Length: 209
Ligand SMILES: O=C1Nc2ccc(F)cc2C1=O
Image 1 (cartoon, protein in one colour):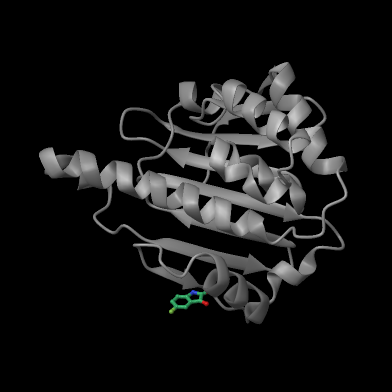
Image 2 (cartoon, helix red, strand yellow):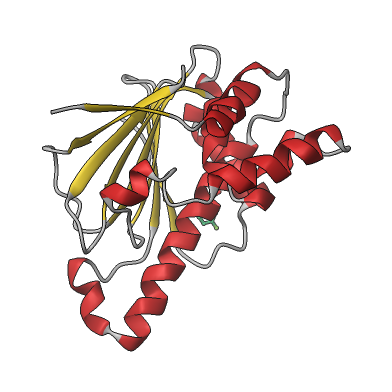
């Protein structure tokens, strides 16, 4: 059972802007996704302070970076609070309608694309490098779901039947054919050290066979 939804008009505009605007500093996508994971890990930690039973689905608060050259995917896994089905349909837990407005206003008022995270819509920077994005998420209060979109104005949501996650979010980036540099160990390391050296959770960069 696959449900197809249409993006809000403002969100579809944001995605086509990111896809079509000539902009060479694409590496900032990893900083935004890692920052989104750190925000989700902060949320589960804060709720765990007043209720330790919320960590029953997983006590480790970490971030893993998993490149795969065979599938040409870069996956960002975190054990954060996760997202419900309502969260997924509601623009992946963001206030994307108002955040897109302030972002597009700034883009004509001097700002550039690298400042996308300052308006809460940093997740969509994934389409700077990915032709398709798959999001697997598991919140304590809901089941495991799979969000997917190749842009084009629509996305799909389905119950995920694959490997159970416990709790957290998995962002799979199906990279464009000319963006395979972000599958290289030294390139990923350089970006993490440059843009995410002070993240308060362990970041493990997986290596390949
Ligand atoms: O990619 C990276 N992960 C890391 C974790 C710890 C650290 F000190 C550096 C790095 C990287 O560059």
